[PDB]
Amino acid sequence: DRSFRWKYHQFRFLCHSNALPSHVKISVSRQTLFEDSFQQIMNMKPYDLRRRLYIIMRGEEGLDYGGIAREWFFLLSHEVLNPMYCLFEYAGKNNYCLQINPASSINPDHLTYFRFIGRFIAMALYHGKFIDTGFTLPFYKRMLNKRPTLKDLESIDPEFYNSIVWIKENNLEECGLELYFIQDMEILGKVTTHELKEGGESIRVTEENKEEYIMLLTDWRFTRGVEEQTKAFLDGFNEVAPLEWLRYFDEKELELMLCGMQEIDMSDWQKSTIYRHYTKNSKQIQWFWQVVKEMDNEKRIRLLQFVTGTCRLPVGGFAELIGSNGPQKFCIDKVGKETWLPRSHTCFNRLDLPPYKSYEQLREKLLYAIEETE
Amino acid sequence: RRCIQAARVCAVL
Ligand SMILES: *CC(=O)Nc1ccc(NC(=O)C*)cc1
Ligand SMILES: [Zn+2]
């Protein structure tokens, strides 16, 4: 019910309201960016990171405190992704859908490195600086105490999502399916079992079990093997910026606070859009682009997040979009009835746009979905 | 048939 501008003013205000005087110096070189930053920030007291940041890129002498800070935040937000640290991995091909590495304990300091990354992200928000690390909306949901949903599974694992939907909409007592409330996990060669609930090894999934099994399994699909690393990140953040300060944001708004808003190239978008059952000459498609033309930039980004799962664009624009199974341009499909809302498949960067009866119908249903659904 | 897809679901989950 509250707008993003209002929420941004109310958060910034609360940061401005908890500031400290003076400054902190952080000295790094381009070649030891990560290690210098890690030590200096972690041997500092967390609240002191709310003071004015003086980042020294030792050797570079082009300066501007807010410009070197800007550059630092960017470079380091990438350097934490270095595979040598074994902290992160991708659920899909071509660096699609970042997630914490369950095997990260092969790095004996991983929990301390994650608490450092937590601090670094809170420093970015607190100082209004931007990062390009590429966290997913479910990761942001966790920062806002939002539980991942059935829809979210399709982003990380469309086949898992479809198997859960099938269970959700079939009769278990009619097909012979035998499942139990327990999951196998193999991390670094060690295979472990996790009970979804007490005694779940012996509890079989029935029609009367189903809904509970699905929501316990959904949570487990996002939390498995990364509980301790995730806790270390959240603590590191909370040390610097109380997580309580994010109470009003949703996950898509939080991603904008950390990534920054940039102006969306309308031509790049339309040239790189592909169509299923529709064409570029379809009634509803030409209506679609009128609704997008009438949107302000804030709402276009929101449309991008609804369909693709992020506001971030690759190098080379919309032609280079990535899905769960590889390259995957923005796509619009004729799916659904006139009584449905538009729904997205973020793994395929797809908008199921029903064959609406009027421009006014499409405009209201599109704007409603991009604002209230995911 | 429809136990082709239960086997597939069962392997995935
Ligand atoms: C025809 C038939 O019953 N097929 C079938 C159903 C389920 C499963 N697997 C499990 O229940 C785990 C295999 C085959
Ligand atoms: Zn996507």
Image (tube, rainbow, N blue to C red):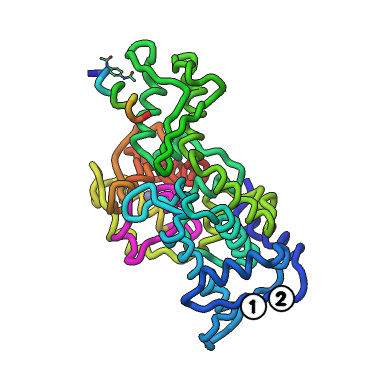
Residue A166 x, y percent position in the rendering: 36, 25
Residue A92 x, y percent position in the rendering: 35, 48
Question: Is residue A342 visible from the viewing direction of this image?
Answer: no
Q: Is residue A35 above or below residue A228?
A: below
Region in magenta: A294-323
Q: Is residue A221 above or below residue A257?
A: above
Element carrying mark 1: strand
Disc 2 to disc 1: CB gap under 8 Å: yes
Assign the N terminus of chain A to one quadrant of the image. top right
Q: Is residue A310 above or below residue A179?
A: below
Out of A157 and A191, give the one closest to the viewer.
Answer: A191
Q: How many callouts does the rendering have? A: 2
Residue A139 x, y percent position in the rendering: 52, 48
Toward the top, the furthest residue is A173
Q: Residue at x 29, y 60 (%)?
A: A319
A355 is within the stretch colored magenta: no
Q: Amino acid at mark 2?
A: His
Q: Is residue A164 above or below residue A249?
A: above
Q: Residue at x 46, y 76 (%)?
A: A31
Which of pointers 2 and 1 lies earlier in the amino acid sequence? 2
Q: Which residue is mark 2?
A: A23
Q: Residue at x 30, y 49 (%)?
A: A331
Q: Which residue is mark 1?
A: A54
Q: Alpha-carbon neighbours of circle 1 within 10 Å: few (<14), some, or many (≥20)?
A: some
Q: Amino acid at mark 1?
A: Tyr
Out of A286 and A101, give the one closest to the viewer.
Answer: A101
Left/right of residue A186 with respect to residue A137 in the rendered view:
left
